[PDB]
Every structure is written in C-alpha cells, then in structure tokens.
Amino acid sequence: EAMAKVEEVQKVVKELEKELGELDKVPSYGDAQDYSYQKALWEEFLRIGKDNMDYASKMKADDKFFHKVKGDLNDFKYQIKVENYIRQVAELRKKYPGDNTIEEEYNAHLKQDEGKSIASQEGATLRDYVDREASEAMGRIKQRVAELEILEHH
Ligand SMILES: [Cl-]
Ligand SMILES: [Cl-]
C-alpha cells in the first residue's frame, strides 16, 4: 500500500539511470559558443538530478519532501530529452552545415537561451514544451535529414 509507493520511485530512478545511459551514447556538442548556455544548463540539471535520485534511494515513504523530490525526478527526464535533442541537432548541423530548415527549426524551437529556456519551467509546463514544441521540431528536422541523406546519396 505504501511499499508500492517507494518502489514506484526506485523505478523512476532506474528509468532515469537507463535514460542517462543512452544519453551517454549520444555525442556531446562540445564547447562551441552556440551551446555554451545549454552546456552549463545541462550541467546544473545533471548535478541537481543526480542528487535527487541519490536521495530518492535513501528516501523513505514518509518523507516530507517525498513529493518534491519526485516531481524533480519527472522534470529531470524532460531535461534529459532536451540535452539529447540538442546533442543530436549539433551533430546534424555539422553533417549538414548551412541547411536552412535545420538551423531554423533549431533556433525557433530547441535552442536554449536566457529567457527562452526550460530553466524556468517545471511540471506540466515543462513536459508540454518537450513533448510538443520540442519533439515536433525534432521530428521535422529528422524529415529534412532523411531527405538530405537520400539526396546526398543521389
Ligand atoms: Cl526553449
Ligand atoms: Cl514545434
């Protein structure tokens, strides 16, 4: 009844462990100035997220901040996706430099900057932008690349 509650957490942690594992396979964008903001932003979410999941392990069902720590785990997942999407576009932009569509979708919907970033977002607002605006643009970018890979390979 309450044990089902804590395991519910250990799992979310483990899901995050798997997620970070896959993020690790995706190349990092590096130190380019274009990603300097996302880089430091991700660095913070990483430091903050790792702490939260370490706690969610040594955390017991009756914690006052049980809910707070949980919500944070949920936001982390979406922060992981963003870092992931951006690592992918960085890679794509280098493979298909100049291509307008990629640069445009990125700048309009994914690029993180002071003001327009998920640094100020949490909960439903956060998942909304990620599952919608960000994922949509990622999909369109991928259609571009597909065509590009097809055109490249005349
Ligand atoms: Cl954004
Ligand atoms: Cl979008």
Image (cartoon, helix red, strand yellow):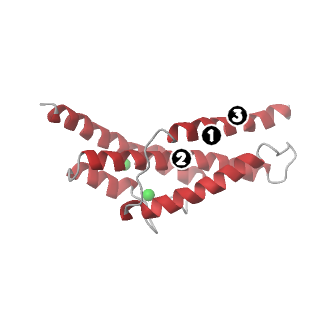
Residue type beneath disc 3: Lys
| First along the sequence among labels 2 and 3 | 3
Question: Which residue is denoted by mark 2 in the rendering?
Answer: 80
Residue drawn 67% across the image and 50% down it? 50
**Element at badge 3?**
helix
* Above-or-below relation of 116 to 2: below
Query: Tags 3 and 1 in contact by the CB under 8 Å rule?
Result: no
Residue drawn 74% across the image and 34% down it? 8
Question: Which residue is denoted by mark 1 in the rendering?
Answer: 16
**Element at badge 2?**
helix
Question: Which residue is denoted by mark 3 in the rendering?
Answer: 11
Residue type beneath disc 2: Ile
Image quadrant where one finds the N terminus: top right
Numbered tag placed on residue 145 in the rendering: none
Q: Position of residue 122 (x, y in %)?
A: 59, 55
Image quadrant where one finds the C terminus: top left
| Residue at the far bottom in the pictured view | 114
Query: Tags 2 and 1 in contact by the CB under 8 Å rule?
Result: yes
Residue drawn 33% across the image and 57% down it? 108
